[PDB]
Image 1 (tube, chains in turn purple, red):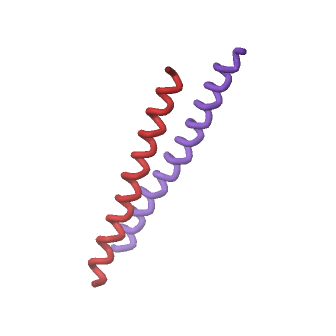
Image 2: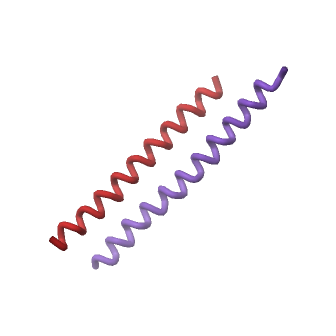
Image 3: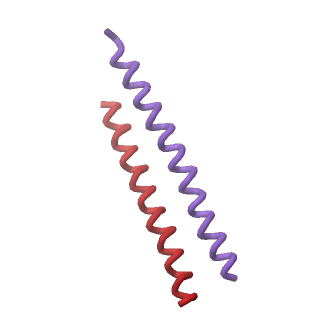
Length: 41
Length: 36
């Protein structure tokens, strides 16, 4: 069974998608506090 | 009381940011481990 590399490929794909969501959400938080600094004049 | 609240909100966004970079690092080490 050469599924080992296929499993590995998916597991890497899951982590890539996971990272994407975190990086995008992280950007929203940075933007959120910047907006707060703006709103605080 | 109001000016102290403004500080706290900025500390929370930091608590959240650090915890995200933490998860990114966890995801990174897991990814490296899948690459053997």
